[PDB]
């Protein structure tokens, strides 16, 4: 194994404590010293990655896959970025508008929210301490080149709009919102973009995840690891199920594979 891909929330950072376990930091320091490249693979836009300062201050991250693979970069170099078909951006906007539900629209250098409600303030601010996202109208947000949109819709509502965003990927790990990206843009695409830059082969990758939006990279990586507390469809997509995050699941999996 030469490249490791880690989802953030529920894989590196505990939803319960909001911290990265000490054994995870120790395991990544050991893998780093042995030459393994360590990559983040998150549905979060770079703008709101505010919980990795411990890995970042240790300079342990070699590259970032953000917005579920639609925005990837290594250092200061953007190696891959896509945008959602404008008509599908308009369709989702129209849908959220009709339904009276919030929706975040993320651009390369801007992030906005349309019709924010308590679910938005609670989840992103009170819970994840994310910076207040500026409010804008559905009309304005959907006139920009959007890399990822995050409608706060349930799985049932989702079924309602699928028909109007026919080529988009939808990744969901929570019942209250999903991340929508262009055709083919999932963490699996992010792995491919990243490894090409380092001359690393797919058979030399390992991914770690706990959510629905991790299923494609768990299947795609040579070895996929699901966190012990992930739902069963996430575990079924993996080659190995490790312990829950707060039971040293990352360090245990890495030890089990002989990486450290
Ligand atoms: Mg997660
Ligand atoms: Mg696999």
Image: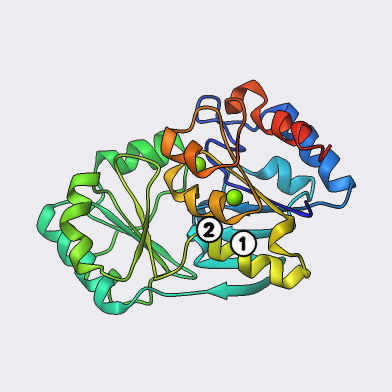
**Residue bearing mark 2:** 187
Residue 131: % across, % down: 46, 48
Judge whether residue 135 can be spotted in this image.
yes
Q: Is residue 38 left or right of residue 227?
A: right
Q: Is residue 130 left or right of residue 244?
A: left
Looking at the image, is 256 positioned above or below residue 29?
above
Q: Residue at x 38, y 77 (%)?
A: 145
Q: Which of the 4 image quarters holds residue 205? A: bottom right
Q: Residue at x 63, y 52 (%)?
A: 40
> Residue pushed farthest left?
98
Q: Residue at x 59, y 66 (%)?
A: 72
Residue 185: % across, % down: 46, 66
Q: Residues within 10 Å of mark 1 (few under 14, many from 20)?
A: many
The disc at residue 219 is: none
Residue 27: % across, % down: 78, 35
Judge whether residue 93 can be spotted in this image.
no
Residue 256: % across, % down: 75, 31
Q: Which of the 4 image quarters holds residue 19? A: top right
From the image, which quarter does the C terminus lie in?
A: top right
Q: Residues within 10 Å of mark 2 (few under 14, many from 20)?
A: many
Q: Residue at x 79, y 55 (%)?
A: 2
Which sits in the foreground, 257 or 252? Answer: 257
The answer to the question of whether label 1 and label 2 lie on touching residues, with beta carbons closer than 8 A, is yes
Q: How is the image coloured?
A: rainbow
Q: CA distance from mark 1 to mark 2?
A: 6 Å
Q: Secondary structure at mark 1?
A: helix
Q: Which of the 4 image quarters holds residue 196? A: bottom right
Number of marks? 2
């Amino acid at each position: 194994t030469k490249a490791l891909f880690f989802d953030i929330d529920g894989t590196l950072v505990s939803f319960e404590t909001h911290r990265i376990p000490s054994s995870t930091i120790e395991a990544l320091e050991a893998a780093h010293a042995k030459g393994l490249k360590i990559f983040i693979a998150t549905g979060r836009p770079k703008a709101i990655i505010n919980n990795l300062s411990e890995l970042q201050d240790r300079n342990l991250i070699d590259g970032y896959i953000t917005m579920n693979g639609a925005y990837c970069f290594v250092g200061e170099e953007v190696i891959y970025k896509s945008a959602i078909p404008q008509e599908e951006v308009k369709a989702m906007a129209a849908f959220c508008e009709k339904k009276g539900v919030p929706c975040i629209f993320v651009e390369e250098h801007n992030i906005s929210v349309c019709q924010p409600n308590e679910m938005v303030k609670k989840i992103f601010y009170d819970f994840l301490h994310v910076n207040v996202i500026p409010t804008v109208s559905f009309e304005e947000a959907s006139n920009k080149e959007v890399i990822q949109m995050t409608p706060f819709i349930t799985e049932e509502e989702e079924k309602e709009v699928l028909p109007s965003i026919p080529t988009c990927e939808i990744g969901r790990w929570y019942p209250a919102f999903a991340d929508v990206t262009a055709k083919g843009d999932t963490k699996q695409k992010g792995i491919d973009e990243i490894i090409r830059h380092f001359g690393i082969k797919l058979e030399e990758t390992m991914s770690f995840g706990d959510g629905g939006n991790d299923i494609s990279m768990l299947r795609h990586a040579a070895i996929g690891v699901a966190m012990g507390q992930a739902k069963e469809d996430v575990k079924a997509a993996a080659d190995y199920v490790t312990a829950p995050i707060d039971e040293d699941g990352i360090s245990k999996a890495m030890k089990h594979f002989g990486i450290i």
